[PDB]
Image (spheres, coloured by chain):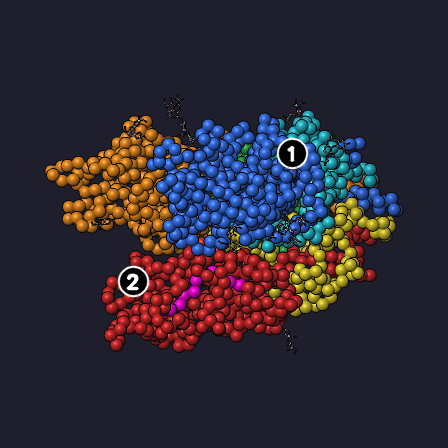
Chain colours: A green, B orange, C yellow, D red, E cyan, F blue
């Protein structure tokens, strides 16, 4: 939860600043998978590259409340990720088989979610996760459809 | 064709504002002689990345933590911590050791003789700030920071951005005029000002207070601000923001005394403080926490934070310019976003492998 | 570790109460995979649908011992789950390739484990985990058996 | 055929009892004016689900935490916290501010003049409960709850279900009979009883104590129960169960005094207390924690908890009926269970995909 | 984070002591996959077999700093492991597709890493993780190469 | 051919030394009567594995925590905690209750009258150790351990392996010679020694101190060592190492007094202490923590720890031989290692399955 990113090639500041430019267009409209992957790759690399928690900083923590809450959020996210069904060709992030339904989720809710809001016009994360979990069963998605099998045959 | 699917980005390059509903974060100062822990004397891991420009446009659920002179941000001002050692001499009352540091400015009562706006709400547990002077003041040179609960809290912000109060004490010079006549002044005096931290750093500084009434210091306690929000939500104390504000300027170390003489056959009390010592400090947050420095604009009607050409930093030092504001931020948690592909979602490349094998035949 | 399940379609109370009826038969005897899946689906959905830790409640925690112990148990369970070998057709829960030995583990041990007991008559979880880990090697299970390959051929 | 395999269910819809070996859980009360934190005034996230019926049949390793009037459950009773302000008047001894709330009932010594059963074992570290009266009782209206360690603990349960002691103080009226004659009554008097919390809520309530000896209050300290188990296992303190018990009825706010008059040329002391003020409270646990309310039966010879037609709740309010018991429960961790399939275990659908492709050809 | 390994068939002491013999040769030079797997199998089994956190010991913890730091390191390791690309045949540990380069990483750095050092001569874990993350993309490794496809065909 | 790939071993059978930069670990003692928590009276889960031999050759980044008589390890010695109860009798000064236990030996000033080497650096916050004797000493039989901050810290190690100081008090008998003549001895006297814990365990032990000056005990406080490193790095306190050292020998329970008589028409003060009671203790660490016992050699110029034929233990008891040193260790986190295969890396067995299917045809 505390790290000294000295050996890495790109600190948190550089990741955020250099990604903001494409994040503008990401906030504007639906982008392609290549766009999103290019926009998130350095952040994913940085958060897959820390060596260990820096003890010199960690052992001085007096109030563990913020650290424990952050760790709990990370653990909940990891638990949810472990059960997500993801497209095989994208390993940096998880593309679920849940089709984007524009009528149900107009783009303003998505933009507000990307902005970090939680008001009544924001995308409802719990409901979306419920829909994705229900639709992403292994018995509904792992077997390729009849069209692909016919095309192979 | 085009197929859009929901995707989860676990580590997005986004940031979110640290709010008053967050629990206190770690701010590391590089000088343990004058500032309590946590301590880190290292430079930023990526010094070349400090100061990179960025446009910010985010929302929030709870009032963000911002420091500076702007709506929604806590204004800074000098706070003075005074240690007074009683002296047995008949012509001297005390010997003084003062530390002046940039910290959180309390709101003032313009009508009530320019005092501090004060709130009695939600008094926290803790040792009350001392009202007397300990006779045995050992280790005088070494400053010891003890957290204490003031008699009343000072209000730092009471507007539509929220109500922020601080139960840490604020020290000032004053006169005890309970039994005196109306000629006894009731206005508190600050021994140091903002310029004392900035202008003519290497030049001798002196402060002289003179009155026919004894000079008292209150409220006492070597205790740093612990602001919290009480409206429209109730959040935990944040005793780490003063650490960010205190590194923005040199701290000034004063030594002094209060002496007594005779004037018009009456006791005359003079507080003399002098300083030729300033200490520069560096306060840093560490990943996943950062600071957004610049023209932070907080609009509470839509709960929006915007800034054009802000800078991303992790450390604050004495070259900080208080024309800019500081917004505490943290790396954003995973997000959900629609993404468009040119093919249907696939669980595994098994069909692709079979097709390649068949084509090879 | 603390959540406000407002947006979800089924709170914890409803999940527990509506599952208890089938939990009776689950306690009585071995059930089919469809039975168990139907019995656990709402609980899994609820625990894959929380959005974020509720800060209003989390920031008031004084004693973190219970929270930290619960988080440690969750992290241990996630670590063990990450190395389990599971049948491809069930994604809600993990069906291991370890065959149920009625002679070694008579049903009373299983019922006592389901009841939440840890006396000497309860199923030994550590020993069972050892057996499952030993028998679930990728080099013993990932390659389909000769019978399936012959049937395809 | 049939193939049975071990399966792991990470999030089963089961529940397990919260035990005395657990560390304290969070109970949220909706009124910070009279009850300390944590605070949450929100209704349950799913109010429509509160009260759903369930049959419970579980085991346990350590004694479960149960409240109510049944074996293995801690019985409730009214506890009184009294704040006393000394008065300079010669005819008045004190002014009183009392709070009566439903909390954990201590066992009584039927042989030893109906006092409390007490234990001196495993005295915890902490500030001892005060024995004197603070002369400067500022902020009298605002009740300050301060944890303190009593002179001796009160026993709440000393049977085959376990030994539970509480080192928090219990307040009662008594007489200083150490130096008096045998006519000084040694029996402790409770200023309030259970009926003071339920019957005639909106009607005026008065309590009068008269004696030729001064009335003393002890043990002092505005401190709430912190029960712990010491046998057959040693567990941590649980300062949150009283929060559940206190919401089951209104709390009653009393004021009053103790006055002195002359009777038969002797000092006569009268404690008068009045109340026309009751406060309703709501205490809630949050997921993964819940409460099972009803006829909880705990059998320790097999360590079994059973209940027929219990109700699952998360909140306790003043309409709670103490004919039912409360069992604290938590969502069960992952479990291991055999499951029967109609085919052998398969790692991947690759064989199925190949078969489908071949059939397509 | 605290356990009583009573039901297990091998405690931590036995695992460490019996593995040190082969750990000598492991420190000496690059070994085969079978050697490493045999060397680590006891430890992986032990750390995949603990039942639950021992409550009697856990509830007595006063200073949670060390426990929280250990849990944070474990969570970071689990997060990194979830995104690693591993050879299918080895399930006990993860064999990445990153080729060992003796010229870049001479054996002394590896030996110092195994010894638990973090000096300027030790293998740079952050840089290695960066290289592995960049080289282990699903679009570069999941599809078998042209040689294998031609051999099948 | 041969193909070498990087592999990650998440749970390797390696160990790493616990360093002074680690936060305190848990050490469990089996007797709560004389030693504070945490408590566990169970034998090791695998008693048959205790004492297994191992050669150790590891590195470290921060100074490892080692106990014993060797460079880089803290030497043990007896420490005495004394409880003094004043007596109203004119011929008696105090009654005594003493506990002698093996703990961390402070360095000595050979030039300065064989006193303790002392450091005033980095004074921690906390309750100062008492300088007076409380008149009301209740519960005298039950020893109450109070954490207190000494007037100055004792130095346990000040060499190239690091500077370790301990702000817990050390108790010794001495004389107040501030106002006396030069004949008042200034040397401190230890009432107990190492042999008092080992030799003739079941035989009566007596200690007699006689002087014409009153015997004083200081520094007071029933407080156990809390060593920390201050150079070349600053680490947290470690109040758990004394728990390991105290189980290596029996603790000895003394009772006694100080009496006053007349000798040559002058006051003559005698401290008498006697003990026929020793208590054996067992202190255990739990996985992932273990202890490496034997000839630990720490080389700081390369930061290497080596041992030939050490033993792996988890518990220390009274049969421990202090010819051996103790190194705290923990199971190593995941490591990265090259591994050689005889085939290229493969994501899935799909090609293998296809080849097998084709061969079947
Ligand atoms: C915590 O972190 C803070 C912030 O980084 C550090 O503060 C820095 O401290 C250094 C060293 O004390 C400061 O450097 C000093 O600054 C002063 C001003 O220098 C200006 O003016 C002179 C005029 O002659 C110019 O030459 C110079 O270029 C600058 O424009 C001077 O007091 C010092 O110079 C004199 O002293 C040094 C010896 O100290 C001699 O070598 C010089 O020749 C000269 O006589 C010196 O340059 C620096 O300015 C601080 N930075 C900031 C941003 O304030 C803290 O040191 C650090 N604390 C700890 C404990 O690590
Ligand atoms: C924490 O949570 C608890 C539990 O939910 C809340 O307690 C509730 O508080 C409300 C508001 O105070 C209570 O409602 C009041 O109840 C009383 C009794 O009402 C009964 O009797 C009257 C007889 O005329 C009937 O009309 C009525 O239907 C009921 O049968 C009365 O004191 C109140 O009615 C009077 O006052 C209100 C204004 O307060 C007027 O509008 C009414 O017209 C009338 O004059 C009122 O109905 C409620 O009973 C409590 N619930 C429980 C379960 O006890 C706490 O308020 C909450 N605390 C905080 C700080 O949020
Ligand atoms: C915490 O953990 C520690 C460490 O394990 C325990 O310490 C052990 O305690 C037991 C019980 O007190 C000790 O056993 C006693 O040892 C003494 C010495 O025995 C030696 O000498 C006699 C000489 O006759 C030989 O027969 C014997 O074989 C040994 O060589 C004696 O005091 C005791 O024997 C006498 O008392 C017992 C009753 O107590 C009678 O049954 C015997 O017949 C005899 O009269 C006894 O053997 C043991 O030595 C300790 N171990 C260590 C390593 O020190 C603590 O008990 C434990 N604490 C708690 C609270 O659980
Ligand atoms: C995509 O969404 C539309 C609209 O969703 C509805 O409105 C949302 C704002 C939200 O409230 C959803 O829960 C609603 O379902 C879906 O179209 C609806 O389909 C249902 C079922 O056939 C029909 O009764 C409604 O009238 C439709 N509502 C419309 C047209 O506004 C649609 O099914 C979704 N999915 C697709 C296209 O695959
Ligand atoms: C394997 O590594 C060698 C050597 O790596 C270089 O030295 C290391 C210590 C480190 O600093 C690396 O970053 C360096 O690249 C590589 O050989 C180098 O290849 C580059 C690119 O062709 C060339 O410019 C350098 O001169 C080479 N350095 C030598 C030969 O010493 C090599 O490419 C790596 N990869 C393989 C063999 O696949
Ligand atoms: C991610 O980081 C890489 C570097 O690893 C960035 O690539 C650089 O992009 C700049 C600007 O286009 C080029 O001038 C450099 O040559 C690139 N460096 C390389 C390829 O090594 C990349 O822009 C970043 N991507 C983001 C932030 O989306
Ligand atoms: C933040 O946004 C502003 C406003 O769009 C950007 O300023 C523009 O910069 C470009 C490139 O230099 C100029 O062509 C435009 O004229 C500028 N616009 C205005 C209104 O001044 C700015 O570059 C952005 N900053 C960052 C760090 O992305
Ligand atoms: C304020 O002035 C006093 C008096 O001049 C300073 O104290 C002197 O410090 C110098 C330099 O160390 C010593 O040589 C003198 O002996 C000191 N005098 C006395 C009377 O103590 C003091 O340092 C000044 N305060 C500052 C610089 O903060
Ligand atoms: C899981 O939850 C679902 C709802 O999501 C429950 O399905 C309901 O079952 C009742 C009783 O049979 C029906 O009347 C409803 O129409 C169903 N709702 C649907 C299908 O949306 C289901 O019973 C639950 N299963 C459990 C607890 O095992
Ligand atoms: C708990 O179990 C009891 C006993 O089996 C159930 O009560 C039965 O309810 C059915 C359906 O209404 C009746 O036909 C039976 O006669 C009842 N049995 C008895 C002995 O009274 C009850 O429904 C169960 N409760 C829950 C919440 O599942
Ligand atoms: C007990 O009685 C006293 C005296 O009647 C009550 O205090 C009065 O409260 C009313 C209503 O606020 C005020 O107008 C009076 O001035 C108060 N009188 C005094 C002497 O304090 C008191 O509220 C009663 N206690 C209760 C209801 O708990
Ligand atoms: C630790 O290493 C030493 C030294 O290599 C080992 O001692 C050797 O043991 C073998 C087998 O008994 C003898 O043949 C050698 O002569 C011994 N060497 C020496 C130098 O004495 C020892 O066995 C190792 N210990 C462990 C626990 O592995
Ligand atoms: C030191 O000696 C005293 C005095 O002999 C011991 O106290 C006696 O203990 C025995 C055995 O319990 C009692 O019968 C006597 O009444 C005690 N005498 C007094 C004067 O208290 C004491 O136990 C010895 N201290 C030890 C063994 O630590
Ligand atoms: C102020 O002066 C009054 C009148 O002499 C005195 O009672 C009081 O103690 C003094 N101090 C304060 C802090 O009020």
Label 2: which residue?
Answer: D86
For this rendering, which residue is in front, F323 or C31? F323
> Mark 1 falls on what kind of element?
loop
Label 1 C-beta lies within 8 Å of the nearest ligand 12 atom: no
Q: Is residue F14 above or below residue D47?
A: above
Q: Which residues are magenta?
A: D164-175
Is residue D153 among the parts visible in the rendering?
A: yes
Kindly identify which chain the residue marked by label 1 belongs to. F
Viewer-side residue, A14 vs A120 = A14
Instruction: Name the residue nearer the viewer: E148 or B341.
Output: E148
Q: Measuring 40% from the left and 51% from the top, which residue is drawn there? A: F87
User: Is residue D339 a member of the stretch shown in magenta?
Assistant: no
Residue F295 image label: 1
Compared to residue B321, the image places residue F39 above or below, namely: below
Residue C39: x and y in percent read 67, 63
Identify whether F104 is placed above or below C23.
Answer: above
Whether residue F144 sits left or right of residue F248 in the image: it is: left
Where is residue D121 shown, x and y percent of the image?
51, 59
Q: In this view of the protein, can residue F8 be seen by the observer?
A: no
Q: What label does residue D35 carry, if any?
A: none
> At 52% from the left edge and 60% from the top edge, which residue is drawn?
D228
Q: Quadrant of the C terminus of chain B?
A: top right
Answer few, some or many: residues within 10 Å of disc 1's Cα (few below 14, many 20 plus, some between 14 and 19): many
Mark pair 2, 1: CA separation: 69 Å
């Amino acid at each position: 939860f505390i790290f000294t990113l000295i050996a890495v090639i790109m600190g948190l500041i550089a990741v955020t600043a250099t990604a903001a430019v494409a994040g503008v267009a990401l906030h504007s409209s639906v982008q392609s998978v290549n766009f999103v992957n290019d926009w998130q790759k350095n952040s994913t690399r940085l958060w897959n590259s820390q060596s260990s928690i820096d003890q010199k900083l960690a052992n001085q923590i007096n109030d563990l409340r913020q650290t424990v809450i952050w760790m709990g959020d990370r653990l909940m996210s990891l638990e949810h990720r472990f059960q997500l069904q993801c497209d095989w060709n994208t390993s940096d992030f998880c593309i679920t088989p849940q089709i984007y339904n524009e009528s149900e989720h107009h783009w303003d809710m998505v933009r507000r979610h990307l902005q970090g809001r939680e008001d009544n016009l924001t995308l409802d994360i719990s409901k979306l996760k419920e829909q994705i979990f229900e639709a992403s069963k292994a018995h509904l998605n792992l077997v390729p459809g009849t069209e692909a099998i016919a095309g192979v045959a | 064709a085009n197929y859009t699917y929901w995707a989860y980005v676990p580590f997005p390059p986004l940031i979110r504002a640290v709010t008053w509903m967050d629990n206190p974060i770690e701010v590391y100062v590089n000088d343990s002689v004058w500032v309590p822990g946590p301590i880190d004397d290292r430079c930023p891991a990526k010094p070349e990345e400090e100061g990179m420009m960025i446009n910010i446009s985010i929302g929030y659920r709870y009032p963000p933590i911002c420091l500076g002179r702007a709506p929604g941000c806590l204004m800074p001002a000098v706070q003075n911590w005074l240690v007074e050692v009683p002296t047995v001499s008949p012509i001297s009352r005390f010997t003084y050791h003062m530390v002046s540091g940039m910290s959180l400015r309390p709101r003032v009562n313009y009508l009530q003789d320019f005092s501090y706006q004060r709130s009695l709400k939600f008094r926290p547990k803790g040792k009350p700030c001392p009202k007397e002077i300990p006779k045995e003041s050992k280790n005088t040179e070494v400053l010891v920071w003890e957290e204490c609960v003031a008699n009343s809290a000072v209000i730092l912000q009471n507007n539509e951005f929220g109500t922020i109060i601080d139960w840490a004490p604020r020290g000032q010079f004053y006169h005890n005029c309970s039994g005196q006549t109306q000629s006894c002044p009731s206005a508190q005096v600050s021994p140091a000002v903002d310029s004392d931290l900035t202008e003519s750093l290497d030049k001798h500084k002196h402060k002289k207070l003179q009155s026919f009434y004894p000079w008292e210091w209150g409220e006492k306690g070597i205790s740093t601000p612990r602001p919290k929000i009480i409206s429209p939500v109730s959040g935990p104390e944040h005793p780490e923001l003063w650490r960010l504000t205190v590194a923005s300027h040199h701290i000034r170390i004063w030594s002094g005394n209060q002496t007594l003489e005779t004037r018009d056959r009456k006791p005359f009390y003079t507080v003399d403080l002098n300083s030729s010592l300033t200490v520069p400090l560096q306060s840093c947050v560490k990943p996943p926490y950062m600071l957004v420095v610049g023209n932070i604009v907080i609009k509470p009607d839509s709960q929006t934070i915007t800034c054009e050409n802000c800078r991303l930093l992790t450390c604050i030092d004495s070259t900080f310019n208080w024309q800019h504001r500081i917004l505490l931020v943290r790396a954003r948690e995973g997000v959900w976003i629609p993404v468009s592909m040119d093919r249907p979602w696939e669980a595994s490349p098994s069909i692709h492998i079979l097709t390649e094998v068949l084509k090879g035949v």
